[PDB]
Image (cartoon, rainbow over the protein chains, first blue to last red):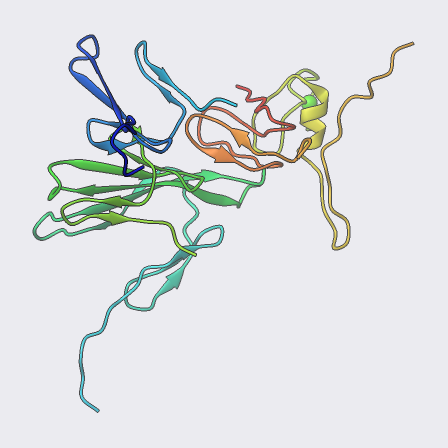
Length: 54
Length: 108
Length: 48
Length: 38
Ligand SMILES: [Ca+2]
């Protein structure tokens, strides 16, 4: 908002050493990127679950 | 007229109806995995198909999935599944996809 | 069913496999005809 | 859809009133479930 005090947050990066070295990026939209590659939800792994909600 | 090579196509449609690269038509109707195409001279790609029987009948055979291997992209397996899904190396991906020389995208 | 003295292996479906449920067995022999199109039949859900 | 929605399986997505039998199992799907046998 082109203003002095208007600040937001764009993206979130989560690192899990448990899944080898897994870097997961949550983006401005609803997209999710794992190790640089987009994925299609739902996703299942050892103990990791990502899914859309209502 | 002047002779000149032009692109060829290998169609696979219907229950079991092929068309060789030149023009030959035929029907095979086998239930296993078969090697559909391969570079065979420099090992630059390979296309394999999987077939199963449909319509609870003796002669109805379909094709489920197609596996593509491209040695250029390290060693990549690109499964095309019964739906419109695409799976690279076991991970489902969201189209479109761009890489060094590989492109996958939806059509109209 | 087939016609051999054995009365227990007489549930061979069209694919050549042997089943146990009568309905799926009998449902593999449906035949369509032009206007006629067929949906498989399920048990009648009615008790005494 | 009420019972007209597709059938899910091991990765693939199927369609109502579909059948297949490769070498081990015979599978169709009514409603939203498979009912695979063998
Ligand atoms: Ca008999």
